[PDB]
Image (cartoon, rainbow, N blue to C red; front, side, top):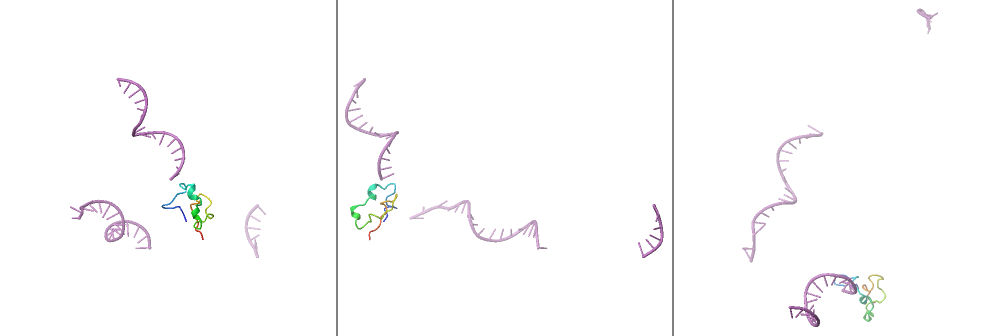
Amino acid sequence: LSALGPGGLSRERAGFEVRDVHYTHYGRLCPIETPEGPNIGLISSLSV
DNA sequence: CTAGCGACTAATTTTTCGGTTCACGGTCCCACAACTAACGAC
């Protein structure tokens, strides 16, 4: 699940808040599997 | 010291593509321009 692309955010425009883990990610977005770098938090993985 | 002896080259034609013409219902920071409320002078 990518937050980037047409109609989405940009790496330069991406603040810290969108990259963190929300309490609503529980069971929907994995709080572990994210890229380690400039794309952290902006690219997430679906939960099982 | 000398002589006898063992088929290629030039001229003319023809054809496809391009040119031309006609032309109605994100963030943070540093400057710059307004700009206005208050302050002072005639």
